Length: 257
Ligand SMILES: CCCC(=O)Nc1nnc(S(N)(=O)=O)s1
Ligand SMILES: CCCC(=O)Nc1nnc(S(N)(=O)=O)s1
Ligand SMILES: [Zn+2]
Image (cartoon, rainbow, N blue to C red; front, top):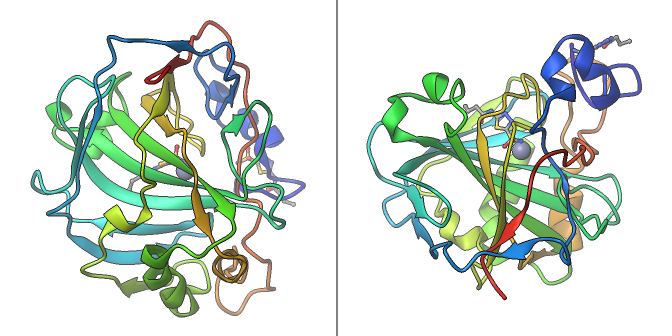
């Protein structure tokens, strides 16, 4: 089964998921000088005030904080998006070292980690139908650098002990994802894919320019998670990031001058 190891990592995924070599794969390097300001892009609308988190799950590849997406409670709209996209989960990708971990890069710079807030287009009714559509998902990507702690991340950090191994979940209610955003909502945007199998080409990527700062202790706790299940040989959940893929026939647009 696919993963991030030497024998099942990103260079192997194409054998089971041939779209891995497709025309709109993610992540990509964001070349800041080549991205073009698009004054027709509207400001992002992040409406998370009514978000209902439910559960946190170690799925053997990352951990997902899952939300109640049965109503329009936490939605993303505006920016490059047409219509309303409902938050379903967020998760991170991170490195074994502070010098790596993000999936998107900025002028080839890798951040220590990257947060993905995953939303599905409500016109498709459910996430499973949305992923079959070229505009089915909107993923808001936020870079993490190591520095000062992120207070709003700490509740996530502190529950990770309870979901150390693949398949473990824990109740995770009343978590406010607004505590994970940076101050500015300036963004780059381009059409892409899921960055994990099945790598479906269904994502409008919105990547914020401003990273958030997390502490070394916070990211160290991410790195204590396990890819393996309980009772299996311990393999630290680190470096669960796919590297940048060819941009091909795509233009990255910037929301800011
Ligand atoms: C020794 C590990 C065995 C293994 O994992 N082999 C794979 N070959 N292709 C894979 S996938 N789902 O990424 O395409 S996994
Ligand atoms: C329960 C939602 C299923 C889901 O979100 N699947 C994803 N697979 N790759 C993603 S990424 N790294 O592109 O945001 S999201
Ligand atoms: Zn992701």
